[PDB]
Length: 262
Ligand SMILES: Nc1ncnc2c1ncn2[C@@H]1O[C@H](CSCC[C@H](N)C(=O)O)[C@@H](O)[C@H]1O
Ligand SMILES: NC(=O)c1ncn([C@@H]2O[C@H](COP(=O)(O)O)[C@@H](O)[C@H]2O)n1
Image (cartoon, rainbow, N blue to C red):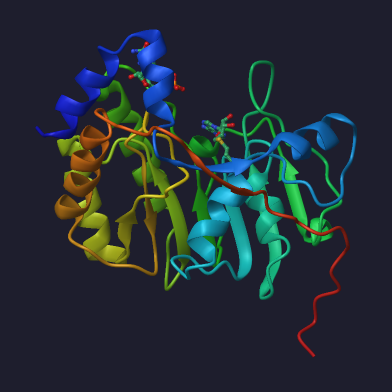
């Protein structure tokens, strides 16, 4: 029921080569080369396990999401979001959960700052476990599909999932894979009405996804928000100068935290 649908078809209609070029046109990138080589080498200090750490950092260093207390990371994969939160000031406990298993990102043990406050377990399907009480809820789940109706389903599953974990003034950051499909817009509107927050586009996301994140400390008419991104993604189809701007990767430190305010 929208304009992002025009974008998706155009996207799908791209040639393999055209596609790769577009996917990174004028986006923001994280310089991960050395971080990956160090990880591959067994290093467990400083490195982010994925570009997700840098991704979360962007929202956090802007107070769009303020992870505190018990943080639950739904679909932590390797744990970029979890290890990152494990080094943040007022965070006490970090629990990350994923499916893992062959053909899936499995959590990677690390000794980055606060790693001791972080527990990651795979072999978990978040959709069928009971909700635990938590102060901040993070969720980065959402598999992309060439078929926008398939994505719309996946998106809703996630929204319903999180609604079940959100309480009082729970802090949250949740990926909304396909925010432009009308059932997803409809649900988002309900949620926003019920828990506030807004949808925000992360400059680090690639042009090949219309993904937006529902963050707790931000507002803005949903529909308006998605169209903005839709127009933007379309504008980017036709670009002179398609370079990606890079930035150093995040450094996650290497110690253990003792907690206890003091
Ligand atoms: N039902 C489910 N239960 C648990 N994990 C799931 C799931 N469906 C998908 N996932 C997982 O969710 C992950 C999302 S990608 C993880 C990104 C992470 N924030 C990064 O920074 O490291 C995938 O690795 C996938 O295996
Ligand atoms: N035109 C192509 O050659 C091509 N390849 C992938 N895509 C679009 O982008 C989406 C996911 O992006 P990616 O495959 O992980 O980069 C797909 O689901 C599809 O809609 N398009």
